Amino acid sequence: GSHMGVQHKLDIFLVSEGIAIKEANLLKGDSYGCTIKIKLDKEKTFKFVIVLEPEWIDEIKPIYMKVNDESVELELDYKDAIKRIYSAEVVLSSDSVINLFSDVDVSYTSEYPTIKVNTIKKYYSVQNRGMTYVHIESPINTKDKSWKNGWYEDRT
Ligand code: NI
């Protein structure tokens, strides 16, 4: 009746590493984010797709991205009544910290998941699940790749 609170749904995909970060959403609370720590010995482009299915309230907090504490613009690829899909590509050349946040309150951010991706050795882990039941799959499942195969038609 009242104990449910705000339950946002968040999934974060490293499409360029074939890593899905499934259900990084706080189990309860009007906030979303994730700290991804990257072990990297050479130059590579990382492509991020973030899928937000916000709780049915009518004031959705925007999501932001920092890379090594530098703000990076998220493209909004898709928005409807259900979900927002954002994307970014960035180049990194050494051990990096990706921060997705909606908030700066330590009382929110300390509850976001902390994820480790090791490109060198092809290792990942949940260092800290925060206040989430986050989990990971590699490769990404085709039935999660939601962003047509029947021949063309003459539109004048
Ligand atoms: Ni309740």
Image (cartoon, helix red, strand yellow):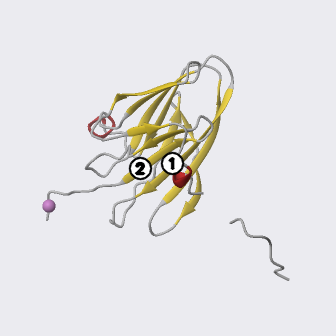
Indicate left or right for 153 with 87 as reference: right
What residue do we see at 42% from left, 30% from top? 115
Residue under pointer 1: 50
The answer to whether 25 is drawn above or below residue 110 in the figure is: below
Q: Quadrant of the C terminus?
A: bottom right
Return the x and y of residue 33 as percentages of the image width and height: 40, 42
Amino acid type, residue under disc 1 in the picture:
Ile
Return the x and y of residue 118 as percentages of the image width and height: 52, 22
Return the x and y of residue 125 as percentages of the image width and height: 42, 27
Number of marks drawn: 2
Q: What is the crowding at mark 1: few (fewer than 14 residues within 10 Å), some, or many (at least 20)?
A: many
What residue do we see at 55% from left, 24% from top? 122
The answer to whether 137 is drawn above or below residue 29 in the figure is: above
Residue under pointer 2: 10
Indicate left or right for 105 with 19 as reference: left
Q: Quadrant of the N terminus?
A: bottom left
Q: Reading the chain from its start, which is encountered first: label 2 or label 1?
A: 2
**Element at badge 2?**
strand
Amino acid type, residue under disc 2 in the picture:
Leu
Specify the quarter for ligand 1. Answer: bottom left
Q: Is mark 2 within 8 Å of ligand 1?
A: no
Residue 127 vs residue 92, the one in the foreground:
127
Distance between mark 2 and mark 1 Cα atoms: 7 Å
**Element at badge 1?**
strand
Q: What is the crowding at mark 2: few (fewer than 14 residues within 10 Å), some, or many (at least 20)?
A: many
Question: Do tag 2 and tag 1 residues touch (Cβ < 8 Å)?
Answer: yes
The quarter holding residue 59 reads: bottom left
The quarter holding residue 22 reads: top left
Q: Residue furthest front?
A: 150
Q: Residue furthest top?
A: 41
